[PDB]
Every structure is written in structure tokens, then in C-alpha cells.
Image (cartoon, coloured by chain):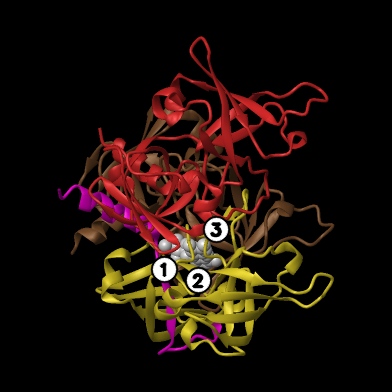
Chain colours: A yellow, B brown, C red
């Protein structure tokens, strides 16, 4: 489980294609001693498993994950090249504060940024979700974009607004995010329980 | 996310103006040592991000958050001045229970208290919410008013009642809350997903 | 509490009737020196208290738990016989990593397996859920079945699908599980929250 609070910005060192997927090495600020093989780290909102870590005793700070078929088709990862900075988040450990909402790291699809507007030291992004995701995005509800849990500030059909506070613009990749950029989108899982109940009551 | 149960009354120390925003220093009973930079704290129902804490070796207990367009546009933070007592609540920890009402800190706007009647050891508050929020106010449904999970009692269009017990009046800012005041309103997160799903 | 990642398959050594409950002795691969008295162990999704251990200097490697009327009514324990293999998990201490989802070990009812279709090294399980639980079993949501953390891949009426990977079948009792079997179900926090708010409509 995650919460959508980014704790580090990582850089992609290597991109190596494999069967069904790709292999990624990500330079990080995390201490690799605190990471075990087969742990989950959300990379730009995508739950990925650690497969390789630095030789123990080493000081180098990176980890390796594999992306697969479902990941490459749905997510932004297929466009990821060396030098790309991404949002990172470690899994919630028992007792950790759940700052945003319940983010699972399972990306539904991709949303395009159509407008970027400055709001002083804050920035307001406007995005188009794919039609199939629109019903699950509500005003003053939650969403997970690039692994960042955000408040939906206004919605018109499949288009919606988010405001990115100054702190987040500093500690996340959203500072370099510009109009025309495609981000990973994870709708609030709490919405699927609203759909389920309604669909169950229609039978 | 939060449970909507207030665990301290903070006090606004300073309001320093920013570029389309304001910096807030909030005096609290919380131990700063237990607050991580970037943490979320529900300040009177508004979920804000901690950006600064006191220096090491300082014997003060405060935190700093920044409020921007949406927070100022919609919440009571627009009127916040030094000396103002506010409700505080920490984020919910993984392993704790989500008993009855989840508060996410996404406030829709301001409700206005229009009447304050005493009822024994308790006080009944009659409130009036913005037009758009009337359909969400369903009798006996939960709502977050100044970050306090309260059951909506009697309801007349956009008018509704909440009942606050003696203990609630002592540990929250509701005890000092008088007729005419503005409170933050957060509608149930699950209810808003339902109505959005309904408009299809 | 627990995560739904099963660390051992245990075998029920013997079933002893108590005055209003049952005493169970469970054989385990867990190191006897690590199991304290009064500890919590999730037995096929049911959080039970360790009540008895072997004597001082004993070689035996078992522990004992006691199940009560609440568990015997709700859980699969009432049918557990000697030699039954059950899923085991140790309790999480504060600060522990969590590779599944939050599991309290408090089951809500029993789910009935209705299908077992192979998908190569993965196996798809279709299950029938109680009426009270069915409206709060959502697609892509989390669930605990026999104490194992699983994701609901498809939901239709009172029947839902979960997928089990080759490793999960090798290390949990799902490798022996088949059509007709009753399993222990605990819905996750969000499902419980939605359920808490639906039952509140009275
Ligand atoms: C985890 C989280 C942190 C937030 N932090 C801030 C913040 O630091 N400043 C701010 O103006 N708004 C913030 N918001 C949005 C704010 O709560 C919202 O605009 C108001 O509650 C009005 O709905 C945050 C929202 C979430 C979900």
C-alpha cells in the first residue's frame, strides 16, 4: 500500500529491454540497506518490484525494477529513457502516517495535461482523463497522478483541475511538468466501492 | 486521511503573506519530534502540508504550513489572524481503525452558524450550507465541520442541525463557536463519488 | 495484526472439545524458541491466541490455540479435523514492512469456491460470497481468503474471481484447494468502511 506522498525524486540510469518488459535502474536518496529484494516501490505511481540492489557494503544508492506487458501498455514507462526523473514512494509500514489517500500503485491509464497556469508560487494543472475513467473522478475527491495524491478542484466531463502546492512543486517532478505531458493516473479505489454498490442495487 | 476526531487545539502564531498564498505558524501541544517534514495535518478540517518545524534545541512546539489559492478561496483560512484557535488532527496511521467517518481534508466551502441553543450539558448548532451542498446533506449522515465528524440531525433544504456534547465543547473550538461564525465543511468522500457516478 | 502473506503451512495435530469452544494443537515449521505464550497467530485468517507450548527442554515443535463460539459460528474451524493443513502468519510489530494489505485476523464469514480454472502457472478461483459481503466486494480491491492477501480481479453478482500465482500455490493451502471448499473471508478496511456506512442506513 501507498498514500501518494512522494518521499524522493529518482533518476533513471539504465533502460534495458527484456521479454514482455524492460529493466530500470533508478538512482535514489533511499538507503539500500532498508530495501530488501522483492519489495514494492511506487515509481511515478506504478507499483514495481525490486529485483536487484547494490552489492552489500557498497555506498552507491540505486535500485532495479522490472516493468512488464500490462505496465508498458497502460503506463508512461514505455517512454522512459535514461536521465528521466521520477516520483518515488516506499510501501507503508505498520504505523506510518497515511498522509493522502489509499494509493495502491496500480495505474488505470494515462491523462494528458492540456493547461498549466501559475497561481503565484503554486501551479494549477488541467487534465483530460480517458472517458472510461471520468465517472470515478469527483469534485473535492482524491486522485493519484504520477504517484502524487491530489485533491480534485473542479471537473467538467472528462476534464479536471488539480492545484499543486509550492512544497510539492519543489519535492516532486511536477515542477518540470508542462502542457502536453502525459501522466500516470490512478483513480481513488474508494470510488469503485461506490460503483459496486450502485451496480449491485441495479439487480 | 483523518478520522475526524480532534486531538488538540492549535493557535495561529503568525500570518506571513506569500505569492498568492499565506504562511502559517501553528502553536500546538504536539511534540515536533513526532512530526515529519511534509506531513499532513488537518487544520480546522483543511488538510495542509508541514514545511517547517522549530530548530533543534528550541523548547517551543509549533509547525508551519502554506495555504494557496484553493485553501484561501474556499476555507476560513482567508480570515485567519494571529491568536485564532483552531482544531488539529494528525493523519491516520496504518493499523488504526476507520470508525464511521473518514475525513480527507477536502473542504467544499464555508457553512454559517445561524443559531446556538443550549440543550442541557450539550449545545445545538443550527447551520446553513452553500446551495450546491444541499443534496449531500442527508439526515443522520456524517459531515466534517471545522474538522469535526458530526451527525447531521434535522435538515431543511440547506439548513441543518448538529449536536455537540460537553466533552466535544471542551477539547475542540466548538465551545467558543458563536452564532454568525463561519465553519469549514467537508462532505462525505464516499457520498460524493456516488453522486458523481449518478450523473451518468 | 497481519498482512496476509503466509510464512508457513501448519498441520492441525489434534482437536480437543472444550466447555464452550475447541482447543487446537498446531504443528509448525516455526522455530519453537521464537513463539512466546500469549502471542497472536493468524490461522487461515483467524487471529488466535497461543495458550500452550511444550515443556522446558522439550523437542516437540507445536503450539496450542483456543477458538470460541464466535469463531466456531463464523469461521471454517468448526469443520477442522486432525491432519488438516492451515495457513499461518506471525503478528506484525510496529515498523514492519507490509507486502499485502492490512489483515486484522477477524473473519466476516465463509466464501464458497465454485471454480478452479488453470491459466498456465497461475490458477483462477471463482468464489461465492455471502449476501452481506457481496455488495462490498469491488474489482481491484483487496481481500483475505484463508488468511492470504489477494486482489479481486472480477466481480459478478455474488461471485468474484481471484488469481493465484505459482508461488502462492506452492507456499499456501491454495495448491490443495478445490471446488466446493469453504474458505475464511475478511474484507479490507475500505470494504468495511462502505459496509459500516450502508448498515448505518436504518
Ligand atoms: C495530502 C494533502 C495535502 C495538502 N496540502 C495543502 C497545503 O499545504 N496547502 C494548501 O493550500 N492546500 C493543501 N491541500 C489542499 C487543501 O486541503 C484544499 O485545497 C482545501 O481543503 C479546500 O478543499 C492538500 C490536500 C491534500 C489531500
The tag earlier along the polypeptide, 1 or 2, is: 2
Q: Nearer the viewer, mark 3 or mark 2?
A: 2
Is C175 a magenta residue? Answer: no
Q: Is residue A203 left or right of A172 when viewed as pictured?
A: left
> Which range is magenta?
A175-203
- State the residue position of label 1: A186
Residue at figure coordinates x 60%, y 49% from the top left: B10
Q: Is residue C63 left or right of A196 when viewed as pictured?
A: right
Residue at figure coordinates x 56%, y 78% from the top left: A169
Between residues A70 and A156, which one lies in front from this camera angle?
A70
How packed is label 1: few (under 14 Cα within 10 Å), some, or many (20 or more)? Answer: many
Q: Are marks 1 and 2 in contact (CB under 8 Å)?
A: yes
- State the residue position of label 2: A45
Chain identifier of the residue bearing label 2 in the image:
A
- The numbered dot on residue C80 is none
Q: Secondary structure at mark 2?
A: loop
Between the C-alphas of marks 3 and 1, the distance is 16 Å
How packed is label 3: few (under 14 Cα within 10 Å), some, or many (20 or more)? Answer: many
Chain identifier of the residue bearing label 3 in the image:
A
- Residue B27's spot in the image, x, y percent? 66, 53
Q: Secondary structure at mark 1?
A: strand
Q: Is residue A58 left or right of A199 when viewed as pictured?
A: right
Residue C132, placed above or below residue B128 = above
- Residue A87's spot in the image, x, y percent? 57, 75
- Ligand 1 within 8 angstroms of badge 3 C-beta: yes
- Residue A42's spot in the image, x, y percent? 55, 69
- The numbered dot on residue A99 is 3
Amino acid at each position: 500500500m501507498f498514500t501518494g506522498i512522494i518521499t524522493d525524486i529518482g533518476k533513471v540510469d539504465r533502460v534495458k529491454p527484456l521479454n514482455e518488459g524492460v529493466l530500470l535502474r533508478i538512482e535514489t536518496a533511499y538507503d539500500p540497506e532498508t530495501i530488501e529484494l522483492g519489495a514494492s516501490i511506487a515509481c511515478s505511481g506504478v507499483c514495481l518490484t525490486v529485483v536487484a540492489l547494490p552489492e552489500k557494503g557498497s555506498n552507491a544508492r540505486w535500485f532495479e525494477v522490472e516493468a512488464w506487458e500490462e505496465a508498458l501498455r497502460l503506463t508512461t514507462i514505455s517512454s522512459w529513457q535514461s536521465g528521466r526523473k521520477i516520483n518515488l514512494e516506499r510501501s507503508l509500514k505498520l504505523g506510518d502516517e497515511m498522509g493522502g489517500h489509499l494509493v495502491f500503485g496500480h495505474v488505470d491509464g494515462q491523462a494528458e495535461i492540456v493547461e498549466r497556469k501559475d497561481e503565484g508560487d503554486a501551479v494549477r494543472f488541467t487534465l483530460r482523463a480517458p472517458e472510461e475513467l471520468a465517472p470515478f473522478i469527483a469534485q473535492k475527491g482524491s486522485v493519484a497522478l504520477d504517484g502524487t495524491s491530489l485533491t480534485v478542484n473542479g471537473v467538467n466531463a472528462n476534464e479536471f483541475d488539480v492545484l499543486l502546492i509550492r512544497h510539492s512543486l519543489e519535492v516532486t517532478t511536477w515542477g518540470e511538468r508542462k502542457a502536453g505531458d502525459k501522466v500516470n493516473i490512478e483513480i481513488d479505489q474508494l470510488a469503485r466501492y461506490a460503483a459496486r454498490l450502485a451496480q449491485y442495487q441495479k439487480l
